[PDB]
Image (cartoon, rainbow over all chains, first blue to last red; front, side, top):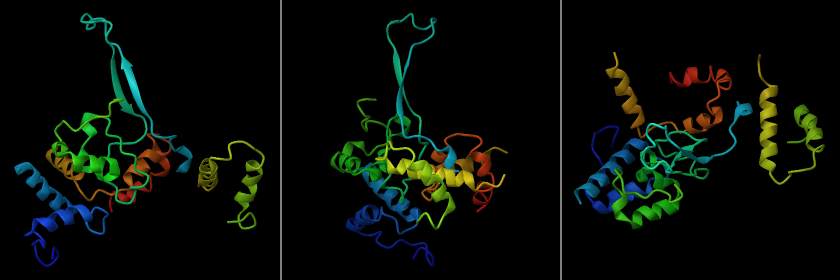
Length: 48
Length: 98
Length: 44
Length: 49
């Protein structure tokens, strides 16, 4: 969904944003989407 | 290129006096710096080198807990226990020997 | 990995069985084997 | 022509996809000069790649 579109799956429920940012730290992914999800939860921990 | 490898990771303490023009204020004070002899400035968490990784957040410029937690589980439970150290500006604790 | 399959291993194992001390750090001796293999195969 | 230089420097130090070889070869050369002369042809392809 990053190839054919510029959208973001699981960008609509908090409980999977945290699981994407936490349980995908092993790898198996380009680091850019992990950077995006880490920045979104950093915006959350900034607005708190 | 294995013939010119380094020995091991070594953190040091540069105990330093000052010049005679500036030690007029408390001349019996000595400053002690802290350096790394082996290693380099690291920015990205190595996903493949996690087992050999000994993270050393020894300096305030290089103690970012956002990536230093993913290198040792003690630091990871340290940062998910304590919420006030997410901000990388300061307040994340330094090792008390340094 | 045997002595009959490599000339450099059979060459340096006389050196390794010559010295009797410090056998507990096997990785140090294996790293020295790696670095003598690396210096043995240079091009200049 | 220095703004492109700092632009590339910032985008490569803030990059999430930095190659993780660089720490091992940095501690492998250990700041020695004659160790780099053998990596004089190893770096010349990896930089362009």
